[PDB]
Image (tube, helix red, strand yellow):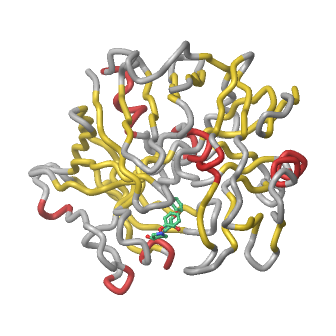
Amino acid sequence: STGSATTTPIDSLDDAYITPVQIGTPAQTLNLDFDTGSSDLWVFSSETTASEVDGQTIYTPSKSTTAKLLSGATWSISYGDGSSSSGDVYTDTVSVGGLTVTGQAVESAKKVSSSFTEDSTIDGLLGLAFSTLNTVSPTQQKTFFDNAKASLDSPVFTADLGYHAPGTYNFGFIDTTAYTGSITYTAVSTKQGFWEWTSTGYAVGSGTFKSTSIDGIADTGTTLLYLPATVVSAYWAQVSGAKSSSSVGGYVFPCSATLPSFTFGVGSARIVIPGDYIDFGPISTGSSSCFGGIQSSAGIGINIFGDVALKAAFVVFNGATTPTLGFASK
Ligand SMILES: O[C@@H]1CNC[C@@H]1Oc1ccccc1
Ligand SMILES: O[C@@H]1CNC[C@@H]1Oc1ccccc1
């Protein structure tokens, strides 16, 4: 089998991407944030505290003839930005772009943090990291990809995110029309449960390429590119007036600037992030200070190749027995 679904930016900045997902019988369609950095499929629901729902579409298990309570199971998650959610668990039929999994754990939120309530465009998350990170207790549950894998034509999914435009998530096949050149594959460590890999270096603008190993994760659920402070300083030093602001929480730059590109290495290959992809706009409405799309990872504990980087490539998440990542230009 295969599946193919369109993913759409939630706003004019590409802050996140939403993909429609069918849950239950008859189908209830929710717009989920596909997150290769976590491993829980959770949704706003009829069980969510009413004061914490503000515009989201909810899953109602009592209206699904295929929903079954997973008795005794609970879940609770906190993300890298401090957002969180928790609740109980049902199994139900879940379909993405024509690909159907029966018996998928659908984690129903009883509580969500204010950051989720305040974003009416995201109805929940669909995790695509390794199932060892799933938070369901006392019986850990499998991701949608892990459940689907054996049925897929090939044990892979691909992320093709657009810049200010829709893109695609495919399951079970490589669309050879969706990229240019060849795909370069690189090794993955699953030791922390992430799609963790080692970039071979970077360049700023037209500058020379610096060969240096940068360990990090391919994370579709993170907006920005988070890298070591040395690398990030070298980038922003090429933008007149750019500075790190403690009050704002990162590097800012004059909105009048033209930003240089940023290149990262994948083996001997190179992915070029255009400068425009690094512009996240005024820090507040009407400000002439703009927020940068490359930020320091120093406070996180891991480097994160988030959407800023991934949207510059066609990315293969190869879930074969020895997992690998592939990157191509597009
Ligand atoms: O802050 C934004 C609005 N609600 C939270 C959202 O960011 C996240 C998206 C996915 C995972 C964690 C956080
Ligand atoms: O819904 C609102 C529109 N822009 C802000 C908020 O959502 C998000 C902000 C940051 C990351 C993910 C989502």
Describe residue 2's horizontal placement relative to residue 81 as left or right.
left
Residue sitting nearer the eye, 140 or 319: 319
Describe residue 291's horizontal placement relative to residue 26 as left or right.
right
Q: Which residue is drawn at 40% across and 47% down?
A: 165
Describe residue 37's horizontal placement relative to residue 190 as left or right.
left
At which x and y percent is residue 56?
30, 70
Q: Which residue lies furthest to the top in this view?
A: 182
Q: Which residue is drawn at 52% across and 29% down?
A: 315
At which x and y percent is residue 256?
68, 65
Q: Which residue is drawn at 83% across and 60% down?
A: 240
Q: Can you tell which quarter of the image residue 257 is in?
A: bottom right
Q: Residue furthest bottom?
A: 51
At which x and y percent is residue 254?
73, 67
At which x and y percent is residue 127?
46, 46
Q: Can you tell which quarter of the image residue 199 is in?
A: top right
- How many callouts does the rendering have? 0
Describe residue 233's horizontal placement relative to residue 259 as left or right.
right
- Give the position of the N terminus as an image quadrant: top left
Q: Which residue lies furthest to the right in this view?
A: 230
Residue sitting nearer the eye, 117 or 67: 117
Q: Which residue is drawn at 72% across and 50% down?
A: 226
Residue sitting nearer the eye, 227 or 165: 165
